[PDB]
Length: 401
Length: 208
Image (tube, rainbow over all chains, first blue to last red):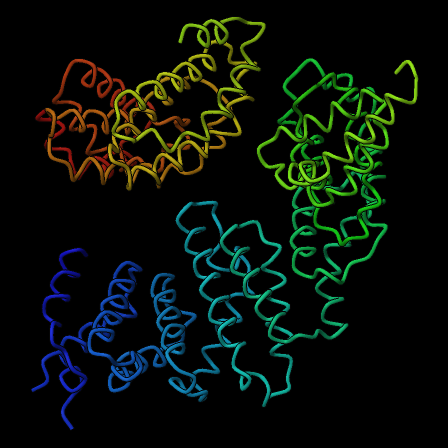
């Protein structure tokens, strides 16, 4: 790759737009054709190298990539439209979808919305909507799983790019866009990180672009997550992760009392005998503790109305630590710090309101010493005067504490 | 280094310290192939101590190691392609494999046998002897001591043919291991099933 970069840099020293295009001979026309021929390869490094080289050639000649690639678009588009996408092996499908996605990004009208493109997009939607067992069967094998994940990511990316075009699905009025959004939501709740990230990016982009959401579609999207949050025994880390993702996506949509229900679940799970037995061992790898930590992790994502649960959460964490005989360290400290770092004024006021007690100043001092508690330190630096004033009032009040 | 070793050898404290050490080590796993001898030797020794601790108390420490085994194998294989010294990630795998031979639970979690065996075969195929044909010995030993049950290894048995022939013409240890494996295969199979598997390498096998 480095040798190719050096050669390309050397041979385009005095390039001009005329030399990089076919005559109405040109030096770089054959080179550009050859590089463009490699954009649909089955190897991702080859595709990346080809597109890097094409961009480098275009920049030197002071031209646009679409200008250079317009004459040769057929050489890539014809073969892709000539076969049914559902019969090819995984790698060929991935390469074809990536090539089409890149081609339809150079300019708005580069790839017309003819019958072939619509058929390809419907095939991509069907593929993304399929199941692991359906796609040749998931034997738990590493390579088949990786191929399936990559194919799903490519399908999601192409559908997300098609969403940006106001032509796609507008002239049909059939459930195409709703189906795309439903597929995005279904992918957002998968067990694979790459597909999760792709779906999250696509969903946030579409939410920003639309600026509004039909009530029925969002109700359908949000039903599955709230379905599983109605039983303490059935609570799992994956459901809480999905809830956190949705809270991060749709900020001003959710409602209060979900935190109270979660706290009720936490109280139910924390059995006294269970905790007494869980002591005497390294309980950081237990499932119940992980579920409790996941529940506590959500409170820093809820809207501003969650500010009223600070005392409840602090008391819960302190009581849990007391039951387990731990200090300075427990699985619940990190999410609690994340939550407390969002309301410095409130936490400082609450702490200073209870200066006489030794159980709260110690906790706040422990919180401040963590590397990530910077906003709290800034607020304390600002209001050191208030802190000293209240301490002086307490000391002058004339008590034994 | 004796303090971790003393803690890991004691029955009372071995599980908790093993868990803490493994949690710490899985965050530095990326420094194994750092090409700085002082940085990698200590990490490799710590991994060895943890695995030996797992071996000492099988019924207590196996559940400590269970969560991390798939991560260790996959991350080693994935990171070895971009490291400055990629052989450290296979020295680590040799240390791991030498400790869980016998009867354990993680054999069930190991369902990535074809990928690991194909990768080991490819690495064995394309490698200059190097610092003496020692990389070949490392890859052959990794091939011939993969942690699995013979029933699950009955398929993928064609992945052991070339390393077996390579082992039958090497030092005493590899020769003994190859003889052991070949005797096991001959004793636990029928001719009509085994002969087609051995056909591609049978001449070299008998000559060796």
